[PDB]
Length: 110
Length: 99
Length: 351
Image (tube, rainbow over all chains, first blue to last red; front, side):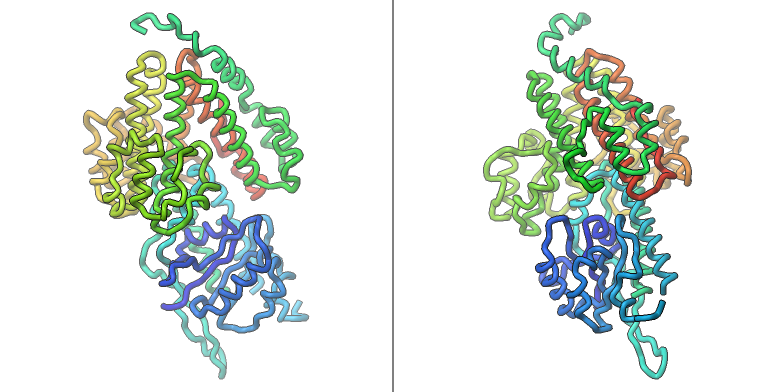
């Protein structure tokens, strides 16, 4: 209806999810996703993550597993249900349950 | 949740090597797609879920209606792009369920 | 020429002929694919490929195992090698290699255009620009992002102005999507190259013109086939069908009326080679598809061109041969990364 899924991913996953229909340019004419290449810094990535968090029109986010590891403290600094944040694997980093903030909230449930 | 997450991982790998095979017939489609970004065909229709005395929001998978775009010029490899579209669509369905 | 070729042909073709032929001797065959299929890891792929023209191309660079850098390095070496080769060229072969350069300048122009609509600096698109479309001319970059300045500066700069004086018009570009623009440019270029080759009649024409005729016919089929799932009008389909194929005197009207896939099969049944190709398309999990059959026939005609030696197709078919070598190398790499060994040999080898 009004909220749009957003993707912070490397080039291949980003093409994959743009191909699945995920993607918009808002009235402000900006992408609702970010491209991750080899040459990026954790600090501006964290500021863009904050741009995502504070913006109201997202709901759910989709971040790779090593990309989510690269920003782990800032990622886990947020605890609110409405901005859902979900982790996905990648080609070279299959899924890892031991590395996940929400499954860390479920402490001792193993 | 762990089971559905394992299904998620293997389905993502399905989409991943489908992309790997789409890297073959077409070529350098990546920037062509990344530039062509106008509107979304998939949207979140937020619903509610009265699981108990407390209500928790949930979501629904929406096909908005503006079809997925058509790139027929990348050296004529549209079939692989279509099956890749199908793969990532199914993946995104399962992912909204997980969300 | 005039029923007595090779009078003084080899005067200005010696060293380039020798270079291309020597590299042709070093082309990977299925024998090398027999030891490049049993890799299971990119390190052994590098070990095996050290015995090829690709000497140590991953040693002392990209220590962790990757796939993207393999593709990039292959493209860089191969493109720079044909820059060297074209740089040892002479005027006829220089026109040939300029047209082979145009085959990439088309998609490089396509990448570099409509950046005005998104209001982006061209220097941000230069990194992703494929090297074989350099457009080494002033004032292409940072034109105030106005489409009119782009159109005029591209007319001034890009040597594709010969095509653009009768292929593009800025106003019409705004209405049609880029999908039509790329394909009309490539139709114009294909026709121009076909005619130019025809003027230089000989082995060159008889060997490469059937390749371009197959290009035109496969194009005419695929445009219809993959335009079942779209609302493109038949008008653009007609504007996108080349007029230098087997189907130009008549046959184009049939591919406007073959709405279902089986109808396109029936139309293609009249051309027996293409009937065999369509009869080879199974589209089933375990066999090849129609695109694979078109690619196989393309490879076959490239081999038939390679049979001859006194032709300008030694310098184009070999370029595509190197493309497919690099492409299969990236395929083996992608099968190593994804562990999808069920399709380790699901590609088209070379000889």
